[PDB]
Length: 95
Image (cartoon, rainbow, N blue to C red; front, top):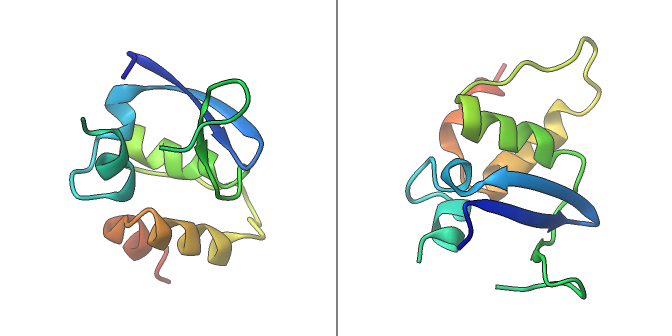
């Protein structure tokens, strides 16, 4: 795996460091990028909502997440956290 990974999430492209992807062991992204579907341009493909991945990705990097005011999609973000298997992130999203 390269040092900076080019991902395609539901058509949303993200560049990120490999260290961020494997930050939480036994998580979905850890299982994927620890020693895969690719698109036409060769980018590794994640079949999930591209917009919500920003905040999933921010948690892996900083182990915390600041949402905007009146964030209309917390329920959706929590669902994504479940898919990527991030128990603590689901916990933070528990009201």
